[PDB]
Image (cartoon, rainbow, N blue to C red):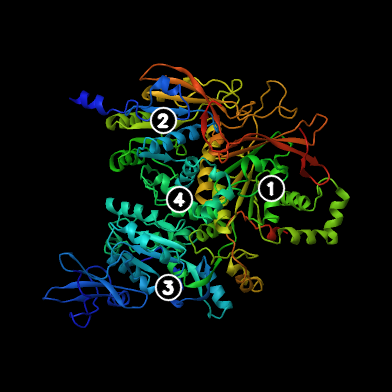
Amino acid sequence: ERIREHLSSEESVGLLFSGCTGINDKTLGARGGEVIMVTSGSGMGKSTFVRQQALQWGTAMGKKVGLAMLEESVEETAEDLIGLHNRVRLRQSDSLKREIIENGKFDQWFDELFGNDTFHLYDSFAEAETDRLLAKLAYMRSGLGCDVIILDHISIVVSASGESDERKMIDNLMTKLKGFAKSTGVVLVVICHLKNPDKGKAHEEGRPVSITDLRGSGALRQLSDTIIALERNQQGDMPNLVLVRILKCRFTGDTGIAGYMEYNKETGWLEPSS
Amino acid sequence: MTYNVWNFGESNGRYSALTARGISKETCQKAGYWIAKVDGVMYQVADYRDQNGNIVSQKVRDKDKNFKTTGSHKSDALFGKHLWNGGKKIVVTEGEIDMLTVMELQDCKYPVVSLGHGASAAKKTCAANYEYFDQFEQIILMFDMDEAGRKAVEEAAQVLPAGKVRVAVLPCKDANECHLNGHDREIMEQVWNAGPWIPDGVVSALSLRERIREHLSSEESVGLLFSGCTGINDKTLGARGGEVIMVTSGSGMGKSTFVRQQALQWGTAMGKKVGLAMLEESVEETAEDLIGLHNRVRLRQSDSLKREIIENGKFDQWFDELFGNDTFHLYDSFAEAETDRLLAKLAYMRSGLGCDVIILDHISIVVSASGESDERKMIDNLMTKLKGFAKSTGVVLVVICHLKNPDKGKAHEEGRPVSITDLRGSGALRQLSDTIIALERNQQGDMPNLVLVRILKCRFTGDTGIAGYMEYNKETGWLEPSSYS
Amino acid sequence: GSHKSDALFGKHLWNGGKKIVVTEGEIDMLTVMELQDCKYPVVSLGHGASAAKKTCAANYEYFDQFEQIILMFDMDEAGRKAVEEAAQVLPAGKVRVAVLPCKDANECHLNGHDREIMEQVWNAGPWIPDGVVSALSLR
């Protein structure tokens, strides 16, 4: 009976990765209980890729998405979603900001987006303790009833914290996040950064990213079920061209390069091909 | 269905002292808190008057601490609201007895208010009273010190005027529990020392739309404009408050000269209060550069002219012309500052002196917690604290770092575009910093004064690459914009 | 008796006013009152220069009755630290630091410099260390 109930409801194709495909061809979406790992270099598209998925899922397939943008205030993150939804770089314009305010178009777009109460976020920025996030991440999942939790940046370093080498902190945290993800069945999307090789041209100038290039003592390479990686050469002749590489997919096992995408400097989207 | 307003001269009313609470008669009389003797019982009535004195609602309790409401107890119910027309700080308690505690200790001379519908409607009550609470510079959220109390604090800070939120943490249950115990010493300092921080950490389901509108109106997206070369503005749209600008180049190529132009430019044309942290030079030397830079000259190479124009009356002229607006602030030590012997001072500018831009030249002078192997963590640890400070205050922070020595081919001074990997420190600064400006020039080429500007990162826009070019005017010491391709 | 941390020598003499002088030693508090004919608010610190932060913090409510708080501490290495640790827990906008040509207030009086003491009660605010000196005062 539980498998019948499982097979009938389980969003196994639930919330397919938008912006590009081949990712769907190699991962078949994001299952509930899996931990999706998104990574790239600094300023390449970790936040932007994940931000499209959070927007898309909570609109087209309408899901209660939980956000944890620990590096930016919620008004800034909402600011992106509003512009991203309306295909504009609203953050990148004083005219567009002044426009929608004075002519009352701001309220218009906002109700069109958040009007479902499908978007829930985390607001603090000032140091989130490990079990002072998991409680709130669960509060979304459980109290607010979210289907997807989005955790930007898996660090919160700063603190000493009394235990040398935070290589265990990232490991200890990832396990509980996988636990939380599975015991509730919530799709868990987390963003991590990449180590510094300093051993040739690196990341921002190209270079494929392997699982070893992942920050931390690769525990995230174990607990996570699927690993999405973005690669682009911001000094190349197409700095907006970004390559998607699957480093892991516990569900399928089909790895390799999925497809390509192009950063539309007008809409702020990652349109597939061009 | 709601009760009728009790009358003071019709229900055995008297203004007695709450001896078992620690509140005297004089205090009860001023807040409008009296005791009624109806049916032989002993009820305590809290008069929630409006801006006129007319009782609107009342909150009546007896021996067993049961609640009974009379009148029109609307969502904006604030016990003591009628006593204060505004000011500097306002204390927001949970219960009326706690509101009676602060006034007793402050001799009923300072604004203190209580919540109408307990800790539950804290969010709604504070939301209903946004217009009123914004007449004060600070809002002292001293709720109960329990599980439910901290959630009420959480739901309060969400719908309160941004930047004015402050939370009190008492060694006991509530304000009254401290008073009757010992701790009259522990309450008041936290009324004047409570932490000015954020809600943390749910804060979901929009509810901030209008505040984002309020936000978008006050902090622009073309925050400031880097002068010296257009194109930097095209790819970064300036430097917002709360961002971290990262400026770097080779040694003696114009890290200091480039940044100093922006500090000068911003503090003159756009009259912003610029804070300087020139760790590798006395305050007089950085001022010396600024003085010459403002007057399009170099007061470091013309040596006869230095002694001349100063002792003649052209120094005092330029000095008042430049620093007279009281905008420029610098750091004076050179005696190896400690990390939390800089951030304290850097915050003092931003906060005490009120600066808009803080400039930290050279971020490799750590000098902090000696004994830990590799300063690779110190630079990372510092950047985290700098980013926190930068965003939590909304200050523009421009920091200068240096570049690792590659020794793998011709390096930096001979050209060589500097990538993000070439950045000094275990690239944590490539993460915490939002915008990264890099200067490149071949000081052994046909165009040494020609400098290439390269954006290595801009979390705001995401538009990277080569901006434009500039030329070092040896006469003016400026970075004039060039026409090169 | 009970030397609580809010010990302020002379606190019982004033109920607010325009300005109040906060010395370190009671003897220095006796100097300022001597020059002012005991007509203007002058107080001393209970626990010396060490608990300067705690004593001033304990009397923030009291010191907040005045428009200005004249920190006339000693003029040594420890004295300047006491100025630093007091001014942190004092009302921002009511500080001011006294700089004497001698050791303390009494050392000036016994020498010549009554001409340096009272006048130096009128001098701005900043506060606290390292400057930062808003350029203008670096001329």
Give me the C-alpha separation between circle 1 and circle 2. 39 Å
Foreground residue, B258 or A161?
B258
Q: Position of residue B4 (x, y in %)?
A: 21, 74
Residue placed under numbered mark 3 in the picture: B85
Eye-nearest disc, 3 or 4: 4
Q: Position of residue B241 (x, y in %)?
A: 56, 49
SS state under label 1: helix
Q: Residue at x 86, y 47 (%)?
A: B302
The residue carrying pointer 4 sits among few (fewer than 14), some (14 to 19) or many (20 or more) residues within 10 Å by Cα, namely few
Residue at the farthest right position: B304
SS state under label 4: helix
Foreground residue, B282 or B108?
B108
SS state under label 2: helix
Residue placed under numbered mark 1 in the picture: B262
Q: Is residue C132 visible?
A: yes
Q: How many marks?
A: 4
The chain identifier of the residue carrying mark 3 reads B
Residue placed under numbered mark 2 in the picture: A170
Image quarter of residue B156: bottom left
Eye-nearest disc, 4 or 1: 4
Eye-nearest disc, 2 or 4: 4
The chain identifier of the residue carrying mark 2 reads A
Q: Is residue B188 above or below residue C41?
A: above
Residue placed under numbered mark 4 in the picture: A108
Q: Is residue A154 visible?
A: no
- Name which residue type carries label 1: Gln
The chain identifier of the residue carrying mark 1 reads B
The residue carrying pointer 3 sits among few (fewer than 14), some (14 to 19) or many (20 or more) residues within 10 Å by Cα, namely few
